Length: 49
Length: 29
Ligand SMILES: *[C@@H]1O[C@H](CO)[C@@H](O)[C@H](O)[C@H]1NC(C)=O
Image (tube, rainbow over all chains, first blue to last red; front, side):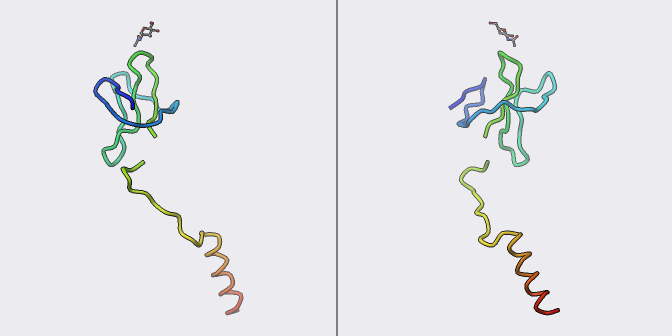
């Protein structure tokens, strides 16, 4: 049950291969479902499956 | 991915359906 800064969601986290632009915090799927986050302390992208 | 929306696979997969149409074609021919 992860709580990134205001993204309180329940998922397994995976080591993504996505490249967010420097200011983009979390990824979003086609049907408005969160797919990925930037960990705010290590600027790496985790996918939420 | 979805919320409780899940998708079941079909019982007859694409390869088997291709085999059934192959059987129908070989029979027809
Ligand atoms: C947060 O601090 C750690 C050191 O404790 C550092 O490695 C990390 O890069 C910092 N986060 C950011 C976003 O700079």
